[PDB]
Image 1 (cartoon, rainbow, N blue to C red):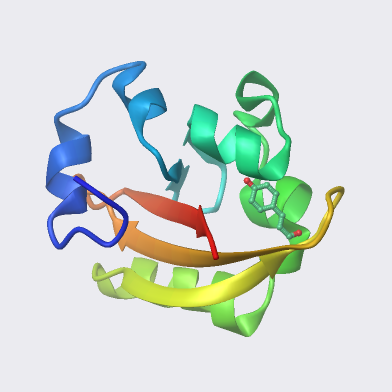
Image 2 (image 1 turned 90 degrees about the horizontal axis):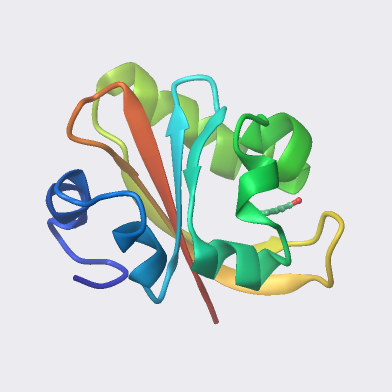
Length: 122
Ligand SMILES: *C(=O)/C=C/c1ccc(O)cc1
């Protein structure tokens, strides 16, 4: 189970409350509109966020506005509208933080009503 694993959505679907926090890569679960449902420890470290605080906020509007663009937020809504989200790219996170380069992997969750955003430094 690692960043980029071909069946990552299967393994996470079988996880609990804090198992998500044992992952070496940042992991965020969003609903179809971009609202944060889950946000693990690793992501909070990478972006200097307190996980408990970002839950409930909209990822694209409030927490990660730099991701509100055709290549990130744009691809997110396409995958949502096709039931097949599974894309990788590099990006730079800079809102309320020191600009940090990262590799991003977005992928639909098994339920097909929620979506994952995986992150690791590069
Ligand atoms: C761009 O503004 C990105 C900001 C951001 C990305 C990921 C996070 O977990 C927190 C903030």
